[PDB]
Amino acid sequence: DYNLTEEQKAIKAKYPPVNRKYEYLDHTADVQLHAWGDTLEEAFEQCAMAMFGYMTDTGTVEPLQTVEVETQGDDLQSLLFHFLDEWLYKFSADEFFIPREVKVLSIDQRNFKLRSIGWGEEFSLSKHPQGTEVKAITYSAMQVYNEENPEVFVIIAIL
Amino acid sequence: DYNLTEEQKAIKAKYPPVNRKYEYLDHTADVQLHAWGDTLEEAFEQCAMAMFGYMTDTGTVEPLQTVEVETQGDDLQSLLFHFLDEWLYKFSADEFFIPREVKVLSIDQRNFKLRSIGWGEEFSLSKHPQGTEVKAITYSAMQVYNEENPEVFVIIAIL
């Protein structure tokens, strides 16, 4: 598993090698995004930007293309999940798109519908810094504080 | 956070900075141990060795001191728990002891009491490869099969 000095190496040869009957399985990992704004709409776009920030320095993304994402939900929590899930999909399939910025144009609170756009380009390792892969969005500990100064809390799965 | 190409730093400064309203919190992760042996006594000691195995190359550790761990629990599931939890404390406190190798000498299956011992030295990053820190032992998905061929799985919380 490890990378060791020739000194560390020498020690290994100096002792009887220690028989091993184990294995490591299902390594998992996550982080919690907290994002906030003047309006609820901003609090979603910021949270989408937060996620993408963990994948790269989004400040090094040119705003060449423009993508919409429109989605529906049962409640706000439901909404914010599919919102982040569709964006994540754009990165991970088809054009492998990375927005520099995401902007939620509209959110409907009676019927839990949302319109948004992001301007960026396709992701490249050559052009863009590397950061953590995002595995998936999970509902655990999700919170949508719809009030004066909205806030949003979301846990995702990372490599 | 990010450290950038001279290109990247240029592209970054060519456009208006995006404004961020977010932060990253509570990074967390876990891995699952699977250890087995001819006897339950062995499954247990192989489990410890896996745990220390994640923290560094346990082969680079020299057998220069000897230490004892005794604990017991209510059931086998908790006997396992305290056993790894004790061993962990040994390492994460006081003399920061890491065992090369660990022997479970006895298990009392009527009364759930264990005697073990291990040989190693104080931990030191001068001497020892850095693996991952072990935050906790969790009862998550913990299974202990006392069968024809004993095996156990335990989920620990890493760094």
Image: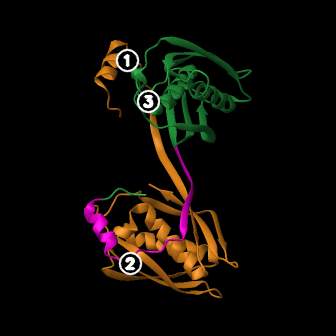
Chain colours: A green, B orange
Residue A118 image offset from top left, x and y in percent: 54, 16
Q: Chain of mark 1?
A: B
Q: Quadrant of residue A62?
A: top left
> Quick one: SS at disc 2?
loop
Q: Which residue is at a point 50% across and 49% down the rendered structure image?
A: B28
Quadrant of the image containing the N terminus of chain A: bottom left
Badge 3 amino acid: Thr
Measured Cα–Cα span from mark 1 to mark 2: 58 Å
Residue B76 left/right relative to A59: right
> Quick one: SS at disc 1?
loop
Badge 2 amino acid: Pro
Q: Quadrant of residue A97?
A: top right
Dot 3 or dot 2: first in sequence order is 2
Q: Residues within 10 Å of mark 1 (few under 14, many from 20)?
A: few
Q: Residues within 10 Å of mark 2 (few under 14, many from 20)?
A: few
Q: Nearer the viewer, residue B111 or A136?
A: A136
Residue B85 left/right relative to A16: right
The reply to whether the magenta stretch includes residue A126 is no
Q: Which residues are magenta?
A: A5-30
Measured Cα–Cα span from mark 1 to mark 3: 15 Å
Residue B152 image offset from top left, x and y in percent: 62, 70
> Quick one: SS at disc 3?
loop
Q: Which residue is at a point 64% across and 86% down the rendered structure image?
A: B109
Residue to which mark 3 is pinned: A56
Residue to which mark 1 is pinned: B17
Badge 1 amino acid: Pro
Residue to which mark 2 is pinned: A16
> From the viewer's perspective, is the residue at label 3 or at label 2 nearer?
2
Q: Which residue is at a point 61% across and 83% down the rendered structure image?
A: B112
